[PDB]
Length: 100
Length: 100
Ligand SMILES: [Cl-]
Ligand SMILES: [Cl-]
Ligand SMILES: [Cl-]
Ligand SMILES: [Cl-]
Image (tube, rainbow over all chains, first blue to last red; front, side, top):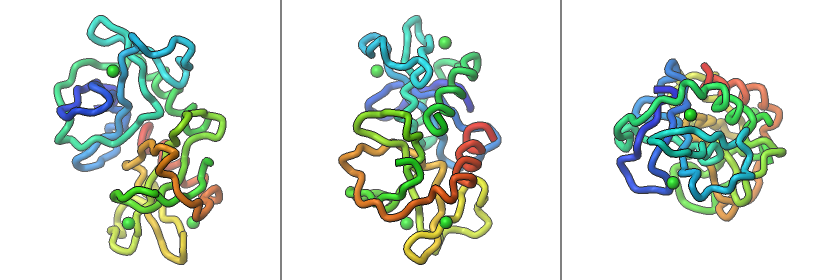
């Protein structure tokens, strides 16, 4: 569901993603997602406009906007958070990536 | 470069992609891309708004908008075409995917 945050069931670079596909856009068996990376190590100067900072599980995370990818529904795990309250910064970051 | 079409150097689901990242958005070593699939078999009723039909190498191709992904520059092959003349339908398809 748009702006809900889930765990990957499968091993990869990242452990969380935010679903960014519209809820009225039907892709049977897949969703378009932006992975989240722990900010803990991630460099502070990195653009917050292109890479928003979000708060999940009492820690800071970077939205890895430029690692956006489709995930099959088979690998979508537990829903862990909702980022709909960050819709503005998510929209701004995606629109910057394509249209600057 | 935004809206240029390239071959993948590596085997995968698709053989071509269109670069859709802004030219003023710097992701060292990667670009955001939408793969192209031969329309030849692809079903005619499929939304042309979400999945535009483009013409390359004297054949029709479907822009697989919902398979958008980052590709490392190491796997970017020859530039084969330019789709900047389809910027309007590409923009419309991406904006529909996220914002309907
Ligand atoms: Cl991480
Ligand atoms: Cl937040
Ligand atoms: Cl194909
Ligand atoms: Cl065309």
